[PDB]
Image (cartoon, coloured by chain):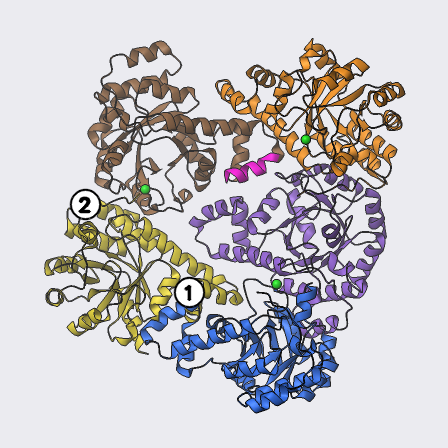
Chain colours: A brown, B purple, C yellow, D orange, E blue
Amino acid sequence: KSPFSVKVGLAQMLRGGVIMDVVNAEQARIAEEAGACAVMALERVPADIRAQGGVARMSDPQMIKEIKQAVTIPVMAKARIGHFVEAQILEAIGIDYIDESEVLTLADEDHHINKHNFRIPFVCGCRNLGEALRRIREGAAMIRTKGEAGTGNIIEAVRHVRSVNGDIRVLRNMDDDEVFTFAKKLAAPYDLVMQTKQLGRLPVVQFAAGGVATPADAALMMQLGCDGVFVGSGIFKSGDPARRARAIVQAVTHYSDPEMLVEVSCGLGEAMVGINLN
Amino acid sequence: KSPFSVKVGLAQMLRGGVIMDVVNAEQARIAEEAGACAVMALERVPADIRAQGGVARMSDPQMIKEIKQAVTIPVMAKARIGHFVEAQILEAIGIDYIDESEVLTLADEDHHINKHNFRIPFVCGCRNLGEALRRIREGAAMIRTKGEAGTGNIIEAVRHVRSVNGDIRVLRNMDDDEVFTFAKKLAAPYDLVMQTKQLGRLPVVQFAAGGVATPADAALMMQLGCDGVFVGSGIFKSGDPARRARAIVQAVTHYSDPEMLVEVSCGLGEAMVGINLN
Amino acid sequence: SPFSVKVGLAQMLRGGVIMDVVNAEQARIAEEAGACAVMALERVPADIRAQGGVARMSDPQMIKEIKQAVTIPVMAKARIGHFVEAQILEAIGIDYIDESEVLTLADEDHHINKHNFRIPFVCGCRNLGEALRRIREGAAMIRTKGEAGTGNIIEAVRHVRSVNGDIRVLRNMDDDEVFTFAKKLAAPYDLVMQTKQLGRLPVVQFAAGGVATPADAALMMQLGCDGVFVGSGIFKSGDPARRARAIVQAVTHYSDPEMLVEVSCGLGEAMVGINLN
Amino acid sequence: PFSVKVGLAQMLRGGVIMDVVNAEQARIAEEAGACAVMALERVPADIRAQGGVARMSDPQMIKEIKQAVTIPVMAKARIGHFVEAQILEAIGIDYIDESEVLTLADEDHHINKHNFRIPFVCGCRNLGEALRRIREGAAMIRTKGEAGTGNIIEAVRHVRSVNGDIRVLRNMDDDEVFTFAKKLAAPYDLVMQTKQLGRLPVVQFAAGGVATPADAALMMQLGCDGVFVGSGIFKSGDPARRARAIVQAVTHYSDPEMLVEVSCGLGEAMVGINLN
Amino acid sequence: PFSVKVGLAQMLRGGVIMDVVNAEQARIAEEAGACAVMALERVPADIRAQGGVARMSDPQMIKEIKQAVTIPVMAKARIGHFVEAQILEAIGIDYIDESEVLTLADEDHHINKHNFRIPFVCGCRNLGEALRRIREGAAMIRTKGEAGTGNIIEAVRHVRSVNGDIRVLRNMDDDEVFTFAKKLAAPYDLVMQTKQLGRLPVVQFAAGGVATPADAALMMQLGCDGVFVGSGIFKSGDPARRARAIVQAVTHYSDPEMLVEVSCGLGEAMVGINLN
Ligand SMILES: [Cl-]
Ligand SMILES: [Cl-]
Ligand SMILES: [Cl-]
């Protein structure tokens, strides 16, 4: 019944899905045809932001309108962290979700957007449970547990998914009297910590993101307990985006079926080569 | 209507009062005759705990019963931080408040008592706003803003009262969007930070404690915005406890009346000499 | 007082965009787009950053050409502490001098004694203490400055939030604690108290540094600024004239998201800029 | 077998074990309702205050204690001093406590407790340490705070640490348990056994700074199976009454009315020392 | 107004203010020619030696001093203790000294002295500090050395610092004064007022370690308006004669013949302590 619970409920519709970053209407249609649950409109895929640098901002509203017209699935778009006016603009365009995104250039180093001031649901990133709960308290309706952006290396996503889920599991069995100190140590609101304890999972939808390059990577994130995955660079920096996109969607749908995982992985073209930051 | 709001309401009755630490029934009757709003039963006054050392614990229930029978004003008693069984015992004795007190020897370095598990209201100490709000979330119905224990030096009480009240004032005018980060930096629950912002004061009664040795000290705490004062050592380590006790009560009642402050301060005996730690 | 007159004049610029211009063509584009004033300088901050070299006051000839090409107020930059550059600018007959940190510092320890001039000055700041020091020296207007020449709004946001945040702290502060606050700001007590009583900066406060889009400009206005400077963001973009207009409209209509969409829609390439992380 | 020793120690659940230095202290302990006595040279508060090398008690004094009571008799051996333990076993006592309050004899190795027929108690401060002591053959664990101070703070810390890690382990992803065992420096099989049981695989008592009935009941409410009391009884004003009060507190640990009654009008507690 | 308080304190120029702890000390001071007495609990040398928390004197003792003399009576309040100051003002004394020899009550904030009708004296060690105290409403400044040692070294240092910075300021390029005010962390308007006057905008006395007539005259030759003496009189062998000698030394500070006469055959000076 509360407006926040409605936004949280909306994002539950994406469970079991793949959200694909797209930079134009052609990428958007490929994503919808492959079975994406939503598209994410942005200026440049994370691998290009990494390689090229420059200030990365909200996409031109014209490009976002073109994407929204080209598909019938939900359209999300990115705003810079703390850039509440970029978010106002995106909401006024009539898209379905805003991603307050760390792959864009940070606009406010100390404060995120007050997401409760918006009617549209927000996705925010996190690396740990404290951070997820802070984003939710600010009004995020969905959490992206984020690894490395633009490298094709799943290592940090695995680390962060295990960190968030691990802390949730610790919390479930914890002595109630110790939860106050746990909330302090997370620097997270106590009420949301207790809600997480009672649910035994994050109070909002949790997707993995960062370095998902292969069907195996996507299925791994699902087997670690995520509700879905974002793919940015891994599709559109690969040799065959459309076939790879489809393979990743199938991998997320059939994540516990190794026979299916073999079939969809077999004879894909070149994966994004990416970069090992060690 | 909620059980917590009832406890918070109970403690409001003490506003404008002086709570006096007492170690036996004689000290208790002197305190009531001088006009104390309540007595605090403890093993040894903070100046003696400082001077003598040893492990300081909850007082023998027999001594607490003797004090409770000797007076008609509310009786409080101290329990060690985290010692929830000491608190169970105190509650079963039928006293009016428990002070989860830092002058006693810490029993749990990482966790305070879960005060919501008790029917009886609790007082807890603090040195800053974050700490006050953490104690309130655990279920404290009253806050003691604490300076130095057992020295007769008001400096740290002033510092901590100014810190708590100063942060409350900052909070009142703060951009709402910045309050999330402020709560993180306080390591305090956001809902209580917002409640403090809306009230423009602490959500529970706030008394000063630590080093109140003279009528001037007591009135100073009231002029800095406290709801009342604790006096431990300053009365019963002085030359004339009964007259000094009365003078301090009057100083708190008439804190903005310098003529009255002169009268009550005039010809008191020797104050506690105390110790300058600098 | 003569200072209060200068402070009063700057109040006309409230709700405006001041645009850095390097020649008379840029000046006319700025006026046509609805700029409240132009700022004559040798090179836009992004070019100073990229090229280096010593950056000084512009040639008086170029300033005269800009002043003749427009009817809106003309400002120009002088190096910090370079009081002779400022004497020259005043003698040219421009409307404001910006004692500017984007030019090469001429005096590391002292700013211009701005009370010795008839013309009003703009100075930069990063925090409230600095703003109040510049005002005491005679600045009639303050530019709260982020990063120069990068197109990244992050430091402007940081500094606007710092100045406005300290002003808000000051409003409710116990009067007895203001003496120590003034000491900690290293700011004159009388100006701290004036700021406390007004609940805002005692002069006009604009944002500057990294304003690249209409969204950026409206953000600065929603954070409480009186207007914005734009240097590089217009003239290092793909379509300076259309972008200039969009930024002006964004400042005028800063609380209207429907309007912000319209002016942002189909603008050409923004300045790419540089992320200093 | 080991499971037999572990089963024996389960009988002490709900009890108080009292340190005694002579046969008089032993009889006071049995009369007060102690589940067992612990024969040692000097109570921990005296070892702390006086220093010197603290060793196994003279066998003669241990024999005198064993004859004076019918409840189980335990006695202390220095860590790693397997010959002291051989001697104790040959005396015919019921348990050996390989004890950190005595002067360490081997800084790198504990007694190989599997070589003995008699069950052993060992101390710990964390779960890794408990599991290492169990693998060496400890049939019972004493989760130990500060010895000889009357300050319960470190016992609370260590009980919360052991029990907290057990609770983390219960819900842990199975695939992460290998790394958890590495980080505890504990044997994987015992870590998995702990995970499956949801508790320590042997009896776990609290010890260190238990001075009052409230302290004893606190340890029980935190999930311990019983408590050791060393100094808190025999460095107090009335050892016999305090001993009884502590036994009752452990038996009735969730009954605040009873805790008031037994705490009311006890004499002077051990004054002890605040180290922090 | 502030200018009225500043004008009042100008009357003390050329004088010696003597710390007194009772009415006997007060009468000795008035008889010796003190321009005012300073009522306090204990002389600084006793505060140093004995420690303890040093507070405002009992109002009764202050009333006794105020009745025993006709010269102005000052008394000490702890730094930041604005209620002690309220009390002193309500007693009807002439000046409050917000004094660093008493135990600091507020480490971050001094008394807002503009809220009082009575003039205040405050201490300083440098020009920035003096100007901050004046802006808070001090009507008089005490340039302070070491308290309770009888060693004039720090008073000389601080007098030279304040007066030296004033002399630098007089000739300074006006354009550089803004930065100078920043570096002093002092209000610009008061810095400019000091520059235009060529001296401190309020009366400036020396204090700290004045033990002999020579010390007192030295402070006057360095440009002070007068001196405080605390310990140097009442920790000496003959307080009354020494008190008189110091008054004469301040009155006749440039007359070496007079300085010889008043210094000749005084008893034992306070022995004091060399801290360095
Ligand atoms: Cl960044
Ligand atoms: Cl040892
Ligand atoms: Cl001090």
Q: Is residue B206 left or right of residue C258?
A: right
Chain ID at mark 2: C
Is the residue marked by circle 2 packed among few (<14), some (14-19), or many (20+) residues within 10 Å? many
Within the image, what quadrant is residue B146 found in?
bottom right
The 10 Å Cα crowd at callout 1, few under 14, some 14 to 19, many 20 or more, is many
Taking the spot 66% from the left edge, 81% from the top edge, the residue there is E92
Residue at image coords 47%, 30%:
A202
Q: Secondary structure at mark 2?
A: loop
Q: Are marks 1 and 2 in contact (CB under 8 Å)?
A: no
Residue A32 as seen in the image, left or right of residue D241: left
The amino acid on which the numbered mark 1 sits, given as a three-letter code, is: Ala
Residue range highlighted in magenta: A178-187
Q: Position of residue D221 (x, y in %)?
A: 71, 30
Look at the image and tell me in which quarter the C terminus of chain D lies. top right
Left or right for C153, reference D235: left
Q: Amino acid at mark 2?
A: Leu
User: Ligand 3, what quadrant?
Assistant: bottom right
- Marks 1 and 2 belong to one chain: yes
**Does residue A38 show up?**
yes
> Label 1: which residue?
C186
Chain that bears disc 1: C
Q: Position of residue E106 (x, y in %)?
A: 58, 63
**Count of numbered labels shown in the rendering:** 2
Mark 1 or mark 2: which is in front?
1
Quadrant where the image shows the N terminus of chain D: top right
Give the prevailing secondary structure in the magenta stretch: helix
Query: Between marks 1 and 2, how big is the CA–CA gap?
Result: 44 Å
Which disc number belongs to residue C267? Answer: 2
As helix, strand or loop, the secondary structure at mark 1 comes to loop
Percent across and percent down for residue E228 are 60, 79
